[PDB]
Length: 118
Length: 219
Ligand SMILES: *[C@@H]1O[C@H](CO)[C@@H](O)[C@H](O)[C@H]1NC(C)=O
Image (tube, rainbow over all chains, first blue to last red; front, side, top):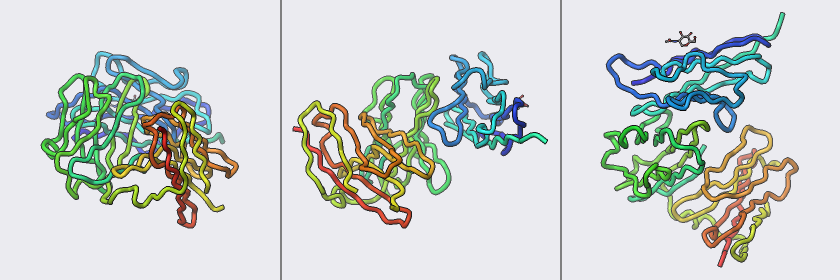
């Protein structure tokens, strides 16, 4: 089977930039085709970041998010996303989802924790 | 937890039509048992339609054309094992996922438990306003009741967490106000197809639930 690997929590400080790691683990002998990656905030309407195998990246606001490991012309396996300028409202759970064929969609939830200053 | 409830029958169809203009990336059907996900079907434009071996001779797609905007799941001979909550998940760029949840239950005609409390009619082409005639109400639901299925048109809530997006294909206008008021549902440019039963379900914190059913007739 194809399984999404990610930590449960990602800590970051107020004003800093943090990267939410999210990788797709597929066995060496198992065949899969990943069409696109999707980040969504737990409790919102739609997605905040999408990377398509041919169309490239798309963000709800391009200045705040960036796929740090996804690249056109390569296997979509690493959906790690960097968030710039952490504010207190960025605290919450985020869903990292892989669209694979023929296994289907695989997702995981990551708790982004924004920390205060000393 | 679900957007549509359909009655279990031999050749039942779980309706699912993608309502957005974005080009599809992949569509998937899944079923939640109690907490686990069985894959039923996966369609991707770069491959052939994939149906799992457990469902190869159990389900098929009857109302689809090229592109598979309509991914309604029809059953050849549906049994007790097909009761559950299904997930119709469209993926597209750059919008992302669009999901519809269908709960299959064992029941009789849903119209039996929904007797009409009011008769409203209107001529074709008008914006029909369905006013619900229903401390400590918590959740309000507008739904269209048919013998074979019940579709949620609007789900309003004040305190708890929901900004509910109706997966009903036909365009309706809902209002999730904050002053506890006459919950209204607007059917813009109502036609003869909009006729039927519309039920206003209020759910209080006690667990009490009250229903108000309007029969809409568009000649
Ligand atoms: C995925 O990307 C993150 C972001 O740099 C990196 O730390 C991680 O090692 C990558 N995982 C794999 C398996 O390459």
